[PDB]
Length: 327
Length: 109
Length: 55
Length: 48
Image (cartoon, rainbow over all chains, first blue to last red):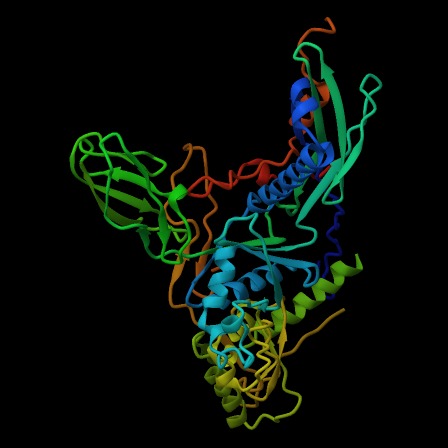
């Protein structure tokens, strides 16, 4: 506090020391389970390690990566920074500014981009033109590789959404793993490892089904580290903007009335947004289109199948109309 | 306790600097930021202020706007083929003074 | 004990320092259009200019 | 109860849920993006 000198009142405001706390927990149980009959084990399986155990461990490893990706992608981001595909760098300078304004430390920062974001970076004329970027040995042109921008090295992952990028500090996300113990009653099990995480392995024969059941598991927990006020500042998400959508294949004709065709929608960046679109049919009697993009034309005629995609920047939905001739 | 007093003193200084009787404000155009700083240098030279001991402290958003500027981003427009405004997000000198970043002052000033 | 002073000219003008501010051509409200869950529900609106400053 | 009975509710699970520190996230596949869950916005506890 501060007070005026020679102030006739000599009261001083008491400063107060308030510690805070949060909590971290184990929450999930990641497992791969297999069951074999005695016939399969005797005749079908020829190498148990290569045929059963290694695919099992690889499956658990990919499941753990998906767990981490759900943590990173699902973290509370109060805003998303919109990358302009023609001018991608200002979005990343914005992300750096958002992190610094929150007094996040400049070291131990990780930037992970999706395939679409990496391609957008290489396609940007800032990196592709060798006079806007320096870089006479042009790498975004001869190698389709950007590597570093805005003070952060680019990591590429196919485990996250292609049009999403995340920049986080080391303290942003916490992971925890526990290895379950093999109980007294269980047949002595093995122990494996996925991404450096120890997994419990266990096998139990069921006389009822004349087979063996194997389980490969681990206990997991994850935390997003927010602030004292509950805000999340230690990580930033960026999303690639979309200005239009197209239905691939153009106008098409169904083989029969009973026939079905699955539509695919790509934005102007080339990202697949079919799972994020809403589909309508102008002539529902002639053709019906599912919520997942599947078109079925029950009656012969001509219909207009329309896909509407609300872009990452919000606003009016982009529309793409195609025509179907049902025979 | 000591950190509380230190931050309070920095706030004291920042209130002094930001609350000064600035007669006119120089508006930075984010698309073309350098002329604003050349204007600042000009105004302070027309006042016959000594060219030494001059000290430039920019906000967070001002530093970001400097980096986002195509004057510093594009290497043809700036020289600086290493392109520290692109590979980093750093502008360290323009208009004859060195940029000092502070989070104590207003971000856009 | 502290004291602070701004050094003005003998005519009263302040010339030894310059302030610069970053122009704001437009403002936007974070989130765009929205719908409240309940009447008791409240939202703390946040406004950002084209320069990303919290205004 | 009985050994063969279905597994009953864990008191540790009930306390873990009532403490409210299990991390809720967003579906990562829902379009448009979900609102941030309330647990994801809770302030740090003043005590412990």
